[PDB]
Image (cartoon, rainbow over all chains, first blue to last red; front, top):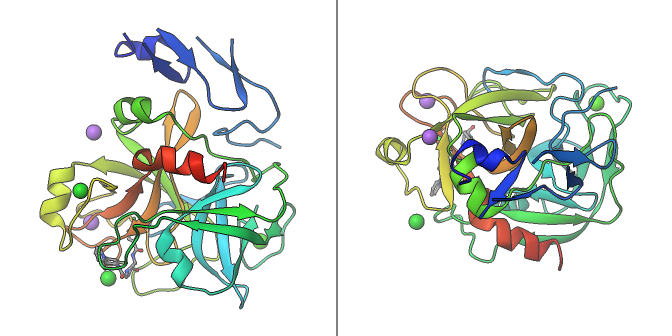
Length: 44
Length: 234
Ligand SMILES: O=C(CN1C[C@H](NC(=O)c2ccc(Cl)s2)[C@@H](O)C1)Nc1ccc(-n2ccccc2=O)cc1F
Ligand SMILES: [Ca+2]
Ligand SMILES: [Cl-]
Ligand SMILES: [Cl-]
Ligand code: NA
Ligand code: NA
C-alpha cells in the first residue's frame, strides 16, 4: 500500500506503481534528467 | 513576510515577482515550467500592465541571474470573485522561455490524489516573497521565506471573519509573529517530500498579517491540478 512508506516510491505512488514529476525518470527512486530538475534547490 | 528569514542563493528558485509599470513588485508567483507562472487571480486586478522578474533576491541591487519576461497570455480562473476570494488562481504564459539556472528553477506539480494524502498531511510548508515585513511597514527589498505549519480547517474557520472554502487552506501561527503579508500574494507555498519541493499553495489572503487569532489563507493547489494542466496545454 502507498500508505506505508509511500510504497517505497521516491515521489508519486498509486495502486504499487511509482511515478516521478516531469523531468525525472524512475530508477522506487526518481532520477533527475538535467541540471535544474523541478523542486530542487540550486547549487553554484 | 513577517518574521522568517532571507532566502539564501539557490534556496527559493521558483520565486517569481510581478512588477508594475513603476518597476515595483506588487505580487509573487511560482515558476512552473519554462513558459508558465502560477499566481493569484486577485493579483491581476492590481496592475493593468505587468511583467515577471525571475532570479531576483534583492530589489535594490541588480544581480547576476535576474531576467525580465513579458506575459503573452493571462489565464484567470472564471469563478474567481472578490466577493469571496474563492478560486484565487491564475496561470501566466510568458512570451519567451525562462532559462533555468542558479536561483531560477521550477517547483514540481504533484499528482492530485497523492498530494491530498501525502503532501497536505505533512506538518509544514514554506512560503516566500518580497511582501511587507510588518503589517504597517514597507515591502522587503530582500526575498524572504518562512516555514508555516498547516492549520486545522476547523480551527481556521472558527478564527476567520470570512468563509473558508474547499479551494483554500490555512497555515501559519495563532499568536507567533510570523506570516505572509501585503506583497506576498500570488507567491509560492511549497511542501517538501523526500528532498523534493512540490507546489501546494498560492499565497491568497489574510486579515492583516501575523494577527493573534488569525492565520494565513492559501489557494489549495490540489483543487486545481487538472485546471492547471489544461491551462498549460491551452
Ligand atoms: O484585504 C486585505 C488586506 N490585507 C492583505 C495583507 N495580508 C495578506 O495578503 C496575507 C496574510 C497572510 C497571507 Cl497567506 S496573505 C495585509 O497586509 C492587509 N486582506 C484581506 C482580508 C479578507 C479578504 N477576504 C476574504 C474572503 C472574502 C472576502 C475578502 O475580502 C481578502 C483580503 F485580501
Ligand atoms: Ca536584484
Ligand atoms: Cl467550499
Ligand atoms: Cl486586512
Ligand atoms: Na495535518
Ligand atoms: Na496569527
